[PDB]
Length: 56
Length: 156
Length: 118
Image 1: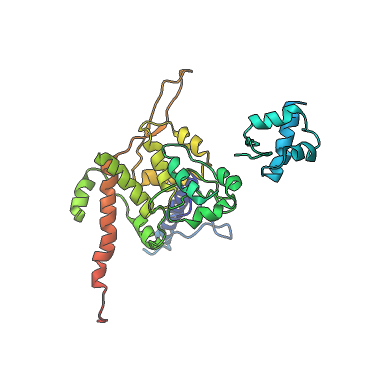
Image 2: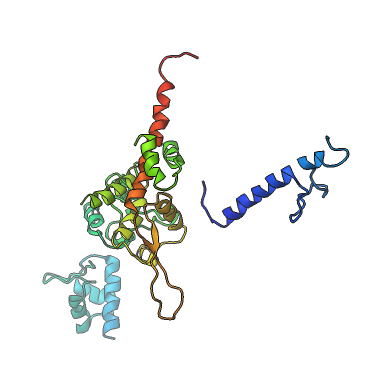
């Protein structure tokens, strides 16, 4: 809505695409761990079900 | 000098900016009192020399601006230069006959509205609701010749 | 012809419900169909942020399909210009649909109406 440097945009949404991705799964290989303000990773949803201790 | 001294008189005479006595202009500047000075002004439009008494003019209303807007047809985008000297306070009369009656391109409201050749019928018509214009903007264009169907699909 | 009306009509909308500067890029490239991109930039002699967002509308409305007016450079290298080959039909086609949509924002709105039921 406010201008369009059209390469900042191309990164801007490609950022948001990264947040949604790590939200579903923050364990993705070939990608940067999305960390917490403790520097520990973020408990993605996938992480909540993965191994023992998961939901299942 | 010859061309330099004559140019000097037109400089200080245009400071007066009106047809003043040539002898005054030959003495107020105290330099361009030679024969080459007055003749150069007689040959230069910077001091528009009439056959009458000492003339010094350097060739006004939005009406002239109004036609100039229509006189810049198929021509290039003109700035605000011809007004500020010819007609003081261009930016007032730019938006005085606004709504494209006196159209001009405000480059910014910090840069004296550096304009182009602008003249239209409605032109801006900002009275249209911006949200509606945003809603007008909000209409996303679908794809190719299926859109020729899509308009017929949409009832157009 | 109606082609002039087509350009005429383009001016009206681009000046009716658009700002004044919108038509400046219209007329400039309407002078010649296959025009070098700089020529408009040169004659307007304005910045790239005073030209970029205006270029947005020309292709956002698809009114100025800027054809890559490729030329034969003398150095034997890449040469092209944004020559706005206007796609008169397709431009208006969306516009009509665009118009229809705002009418839908009124044709639907007729049910949002006078007498209180809720």
